Image: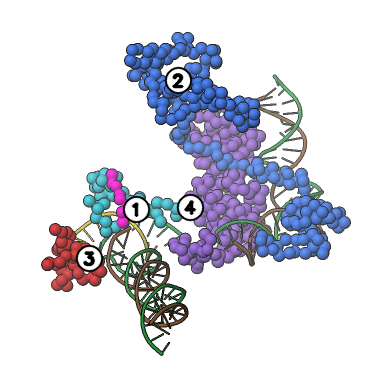
Chain colours: A blue, B cyan, C purple, D red, E green, F yellow, G brown
Amino acid sequence: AERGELDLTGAKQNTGVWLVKVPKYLSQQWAKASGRGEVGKLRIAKTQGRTEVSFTLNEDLANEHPFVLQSVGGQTLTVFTESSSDKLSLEGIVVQRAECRPAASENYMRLKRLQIEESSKPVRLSQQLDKVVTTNYKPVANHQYNIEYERKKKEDGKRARADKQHVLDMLFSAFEKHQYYNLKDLVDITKQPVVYLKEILKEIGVQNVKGIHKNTWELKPE
Amino acid sequence: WGDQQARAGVSQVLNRLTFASTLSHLRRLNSPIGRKLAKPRQ
Amino acid sequence: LSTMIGKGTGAASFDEFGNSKYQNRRTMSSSDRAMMNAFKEITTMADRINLPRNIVDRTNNLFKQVYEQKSLKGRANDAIASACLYIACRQEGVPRTFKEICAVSRISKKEIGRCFKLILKALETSVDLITTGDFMSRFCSNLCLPKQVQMAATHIARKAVELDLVPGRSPISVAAAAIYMASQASAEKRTQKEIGDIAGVADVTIRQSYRLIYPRAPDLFPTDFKFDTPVDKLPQL
Amino acid sequence: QSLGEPATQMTLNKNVTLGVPRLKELINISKKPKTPSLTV
DNA sequence: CTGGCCCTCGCTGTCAAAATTGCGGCTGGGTGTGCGCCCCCACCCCCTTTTATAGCCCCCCTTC
RNA sequence: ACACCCAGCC
DNA sequence: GAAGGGGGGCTATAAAAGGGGGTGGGGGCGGCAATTTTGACAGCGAGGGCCAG
């Protein structure tokens, strides 16, 4: 008993299942039934030396499909199941392969044409304009993004110069938070004028050259 | 034919000396073989 | 006077790890690179409104003159370029409205106007005053109106300006009102939204220009024009 | 000139190489021939 | 001191691959064409207040 | 200039 | 809820204050086809040392 164990009762019973290949129209019709319970019937006849297989469509669903059997020994076809409880089980092994073909030959090509037409509905190709487009690059006093940015800039305003002790308090919180820093991020965190930050940082801080990215300031007084 | 190791002579000035000349030019095929190799010429 | 280095051709051209040992280290000045950036931006700006190359060349000339004269170092090169494009368009007799140059630039009407004023001061030159006529072929064609309407609008705007019916109104506003009140006289009709968005004028600007131009309706039209609509049938806002 | 003027008239190609290719074969060293032979 | 044998080692021939230059002679047309990132340092513009002026234009209010 | 076509005669 | 209307801000100039922030200008960091040459390899010679001679 385990999550990944595969149950093999079906194999021990040697249950034989049928693998059937059907076209799109039959599957779509069966899906349209909304799981009513029945969608058709299958007729298997056995003569003295031959076997005939066919599928009879339900008359209600519409408002004769011959079946061809193929070789089975080419590959070992089986089926397994996975559930919401993460339990793996093997339903069984495929014992025979089936191919479904339409009885109609010429009139079914009309349905094929309709299917192709439906498949070509969403494919897009360029159109042609009778008149040149003039709705673009329309004159405007100012761009929307620009006026938005100026409105934001004038609501927030300039970052106000503060006394030395309080900016030093932000610096103290800063190199308590992290050892190393980048000049831009320090400006963003402290919210102070860049020249005033440089003036108050040069007195206590020093710049250390690095061969990896760029020279940077150090918040340690020593 | 490419950005401003590329094919050259893909586009040519249409020949307007005679109507037969224009038709012949509009229906021409070019082989990119260098201009040696007698087999592609046959 | 400089030359480029082409792509590598063999093993000797490359280095130990997937990179060429010779690179396109250009020796361009800051000045030449900044003004080439500006010419490239001017061409992009001009092709947005389908200006011919001669206006682009005139704009390049004005930009070079300003950039050598060196009096506007503090203004963005893109604003100087926009103002130069405006001056070049105005000098060729095919002026574009300030809002039209704004629409193809990141630079506002405030900033391009200030740079235009400052460029005119620096170059010690002058430009002809715009007449409600030059802004007609475009503002109409873009709105798709017949040629008899071209003549009607041109004549009527010129006559309205000539006899000083409209005091101090900008030529754009008078031109747009002419287009409005010559369009309804023909079969082809145009609402306020189209003319406003295609000429740059607001609805209140075009409405009060219409109410100013309305009373002298019949005397202002050209004599030889097909009145598809009666003169008294024009709707008053 | 007297040996190069006939060369303009000769054509190209048991098989024994002859014509302009053999003239190239002869006036060069050609350490590897085209059609070696021995008249034994 | 003399002679028979196998060893590391020096040198050579031989094969192979990479590297190299040229590929007819004249002629007549036409047609086109001419970095890049990220940072640091000087200099200038806008922030704000005042007031007159007027056309233009956004926003809110009101109508039906 | 340069380049690219085309073409003429062998 | 679309249309017309009213009130009010935006636009340009003007001097001036001081400083922040934007902008440029640095600015260093970042095809055939015979020949020719060289090398790599497989091989081989003479001699050394050992053992015998």
Q: Is residue B17 above or below residue C36?
A: above
Q: Which residue is mark 1?
A: B9
Specify the segment rendered in magenta: B27-34
Q: Which residue is mark 3?
A: D33
| Residue C19 picture location, percent across and down | 52, 61
Numbered badge on residue C53: 4
Q: Of discs 2 and 1, which sits in the foreground?
A: 2
Residue at image x 71%, y 46%?
A150
Q: Which residue is mark 2?
A: A25
Residue at image x 56%, y 57%?
C37
Mark 2: secondary structure: helix
Mark 4: secondary structure: helix
**How far apart, in angstroms, are the residues tagged by discs 2 and 1?**
53 Å
Q: Chain of mark 1?
A: B
Q: Is residue A70 left or right of residue G12?
A: left
Q: Of discs 2 and 4, which sits in the foreground?
A: 2
Indicate the quadrant containing the N terminus of chain A: top left, top right, bottom left or bottom right: top right
